Structure formats: C-alpha cells, structure tokens
Length: 438
Ligand SMILES: [K+]
Image (cartoon, rainbow, N blue to C red; front, side):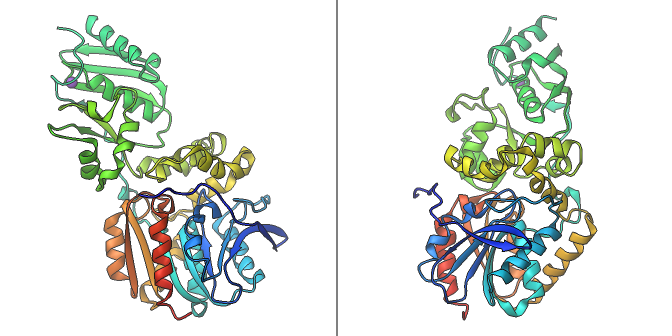
C-alpha cells in the first residue's frame, strides 16, 4: 500500500570488459561482502532500483547491465547465453570481487546459478525469484482450447426477437470490437460462424467472446484464421454473485489481478460492475504455450520481438500485475529504441531449456539445479501468484526440496516481482543477510 518509485538515482559506473564497456550500479560501503544483483530479459539494473535502497545503507550493492542491455555497450554478438556467461565472468573479475551474495532474477538467475555452481566457495547466499529451470515438455503451459465454443444461450445483448448475421456484425461494428471489419458472420439455429483472416489472436478472442455474448447465440464456430498466435486466453463464464476479484481469485489464485481481466475484455466490457451472469470473458493465461512457441522461430519470432518490439511492449507489461507508468515504460524502452539492438531479446527466449532444446543449455541448467539441490548455501526464494516462470506449486516444491531455503510469498506477482512488491523483497533481503556469516 505504498508508492513505488519510478526514478533511477544511481550514479553511472562503467568498466572495460573484454574490450566492451559495461554499465553498473555501485552503492553502499566499499569493503564488506557485496551483493551482486543480476537482471534478466528484457530488463536492466532499473528493475532493482527500489530493492537496493533497503540494503545499501549496510552492504555494497553492485548491479550490472548485461552486455547488449541497459546502458552497457552493444557489440555485434549473437547474444547467446555463453556470450553473457563470458562477459559476466569477466565483469566479476574486473571488479575484483571475491566472495559475493547473489540476488538474481530470470536469465540473471541462470547466470548466477551457473557461476555459483562453478565457484561455490565464493557464494555466501543466493536470493532468487522467477528463475530458469529445465522444462521437460511443452504441455507445462496451457494452450488455446479449440472451438466450437459454447455460451449460455439466453445471456448477453438482445439484438432481435441472413438477417441474424447482419445484426451480429453491425453490433460488433457499433461496439467497436477491434478488427470487426475483417470478419464475416453466419448465424443458423443459435450457431454463429465467424470467418476471416489476418487477425491477431487477441482480436480473434475479443470477436469470439463478443459474438457469444449475444442473446440467442448458443455456440460460435471458429473459422478465424490468425497470424501465428503469440498469446492465448481461456474463456470463463460469469456466475451469479461473481465479481472480477472473485474471478481473479478462482482463475489466477489471487484476487488482485482483477484489472487484468477488465482490460482484457475492453471495449465490450465498460466497467467491472457491468459483468452479468452467463457472460463469457477472456482471461489471458499468465504464460501461454503459444508465446514461446512463436518466439522460438526465425520468422514469426523475429518479426514479433525485433520488428514489433513485443517483448518490451507486450510481454513486459504482462509480467507485472500493476500497470507500469509511461515513465517506467520509457526506462525499459530506452536501450531498445533501435530494432537492430533487439537481438538479445530474441535470443534469450530461444535459449530457454524447453523439451530438450537447446541441448547445451538444458545440460547446464540441469547441472546447476543438481548442484543447488545438494548445496547447503543459504537460499532465499521469492514467489508470487500466479507467477510466470515459477508458479506457486513449483515454488512450494522447491521450498521443501532445496536445503537451507527460506521462501517468501510476495502476494500477486507475474514475472517482475520487483515491480509488484519491492518493499517486501528489499526488506526481506535486508533481514536475511544477518543470517549469512559475511
Ligand atoms: K449467448
């Protein structure tokens, strides 16, 4: 219940690493065991801005921008994980760090765990969140369920007591359902067919739900040919007594993602109070199978992430429960204003260890998971609900599996837990350091 700062009031520091300049934050005292904060994709040290001030009064905090990100230089690299390994190894040695406490997130966690496995004597504790683990099968993530889609026939807008299809299309047009101009409608015995192509997955889902939410429409036959889908939702039927908060609790496991559901159902839904029993709503998956399937290709994936900047304009806001402000979005946008600079954002999801590929990353991540499961190193695991990379059920398993591990529930959270509860994360790190022997 407190304001979250947007500013980045850290003096810039730069250091030569393998002939390139890396930017880093360096605050706090000069001489103790330092904390090394490692960010992931598509962030920078900016993601740590509201955590570090909880620790900097008593401990040195070092937060680098990965090569090719933040304010670091942008060499002509493929930006494979191994590139990041080489630069981060050289960064640590260029600063003369000996012993460290790691605080790591997302791809920063693969860097930190891989460095800790190789240098276990130099790691005094690891705080981590929304981290990389091997995913054995694609069915770890949900997929868009294929139609036909069934609706509560009598529920929705009454358009009446060839004619039916026209009233449906004009209703989509008048209510401003995006890309209604691209679809045509057929209605027969309460069954609607929606046909078209060139629609995004989001636009198609909004059209499908809007057609189903007409009084007298019992089912919608889905003939809408999309681009390659890069997100997906489930369809939820509103019950009597429902609120968006109750629906969020049921589907996401936490009530505080209510505004995500509201936003996902505009323009057809005008305010949260206006849901009605029998209404269908789209509820975006926290992480759809479609997303990394689309990203992990050299045609669709590069068009989305390089040409359209989807990791910054779409995926990043979907990784935060609260709405990011324009000031915050601009800080995240700044290193990637040129598309030619977006290579790391595409290579990173293509390095994720999913279903055996890429083999080198799968092996390396299994290796540091094996190390972590037998290591007595102090561990602090932050998790949120519903999560993205680490859902609550996985967090619970790891809290019991990992030795010497304290787990902290931060409340609602997706991928950037630092953007949803920085005060809890910073103050829990600060209290945990006193148990480390540093
Ligand atoms: K209906």
